[PDB]
Length: 109
Ligand SMILES: [Au+]
Ligand SMILES: [Au+]
Image (cartoon, rainbow, N blue to C red; front, side, top):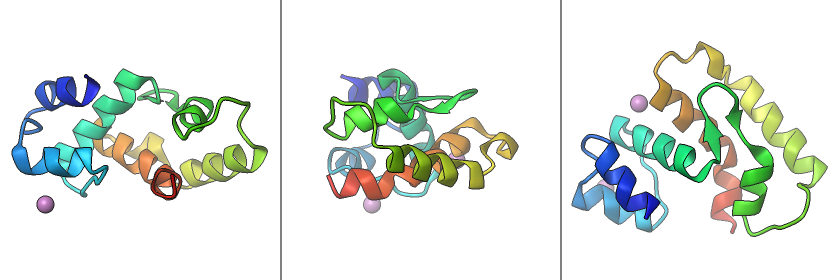
C-alpha cells in the first residue's frame, strides 16, 4: 500500500520504469527516487527528517524481532554520523543519503 501511495505522493514517482525498480527493491540515484525513498521511510516509520533513521525499526524490517545487535547499531550510527545529514538541506536527498548506510543490510536479506 505504501509503495503505491508513495508513487502518488511523490511527483514523477507514478512511473512504470521506476516502479519496476522499486518492486525489485532497486533504488537508483535520482531525485524522484530520493523522494520516493523518503516517503516510504516516513510511511513505514523507518525514518524521520529531524531524528533520522530508527535503527531498531529497521532491524525489525530486516526480519528480526529482538533488540538490535550492538554491532548493527554501532555501525550504522557511525555511517550516518559520517554523512552529516544535518548539512543536507534538501530533505529527499538527506533521506536517500541516510538509507544508503543500510543498503548492504537490505540486499543481503
Ligand atoms: Au532504469
Ligand atoms: Au534528490
